[PDB]
Image (cartoon, rainbow, N blue to C red; front, side):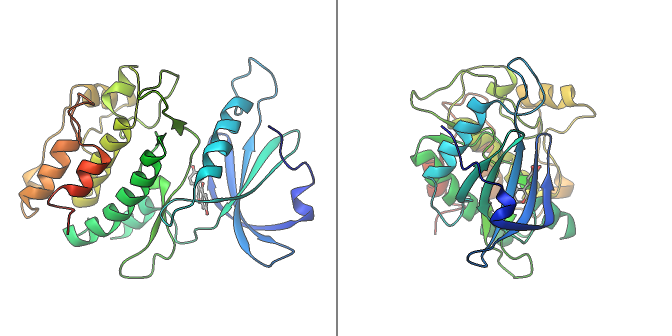
Amino acid sequence: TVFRQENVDDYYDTGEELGSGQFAVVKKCREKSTGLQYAAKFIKKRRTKSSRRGVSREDIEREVSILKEIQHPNVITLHEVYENKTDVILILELVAGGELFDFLAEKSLTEEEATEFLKQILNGVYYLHSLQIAHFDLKPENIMLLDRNVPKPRIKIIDFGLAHKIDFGNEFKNIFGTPEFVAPEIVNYEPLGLEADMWSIGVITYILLSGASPFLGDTKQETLANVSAVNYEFEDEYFSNTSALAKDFIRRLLVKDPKKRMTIQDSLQHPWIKP
Ligand SMILES: O=c1c(-c2ccc(O)c(O)c2)coc2cc(O)ccc12
């Protein structure tokens, strides 16, 4: 599949940088014809077949195809795609309230505040998993607030760079995200499905409640070893006044066997979440 090959700057003016990763940089932008604002994600293309810098066209095409399916209040949307020889440029919905990660660094949250975010995250993941879309990169840096200066911020899930459609219940590729948030099946290079996202949600929930990361080691590999062993515990110093039901929620997500792990539907019916 090919994308619009006109110069993006003939149609948009760019502004503040919103994020910068390994192969992508995201810039605030404004469409000339409408005055409407977006976020332009510039993704570096691979320059040769066997190269290791940049993103493969197959990977970019998968990301675009997935993004095109999405319309939901808690998930980022795609407006337009441009390309040239160097980059593919995704014109994405603008979310201007910054990362949940940076937000958490200001405020630990109360259980009510934690569930305020969690419920939106769960609604967004429910949508994705209903479409057999596994995100595979759920973490606080990939949850964006619309407005961080309101008591109950609205959020959107971003970054579909590792997302996959799971049409056979499981998938077997090179997929591997951030050690603190990856499920044991990813660590052990086993077939992956929708369940891996649910583990990541357990990790996110632990962090929201405590301000600490449950599996974090001194190095990348030690974190990975902790994940595979399910080496975590609820520190009394952090959880002494947290409800046992909140711990129960996390406990049913941080489960090594993906088939024993709570599904997105289970999590929405869990007594801690369910109204
Ligand atoms: O994708 C993003 C990122 C982003 C955050 C961290 C990264 O490492 C990265 O490469 C990109 C930040 O702000 C955004 C705002 C949007 O409206 C859409 C997408 C993004």
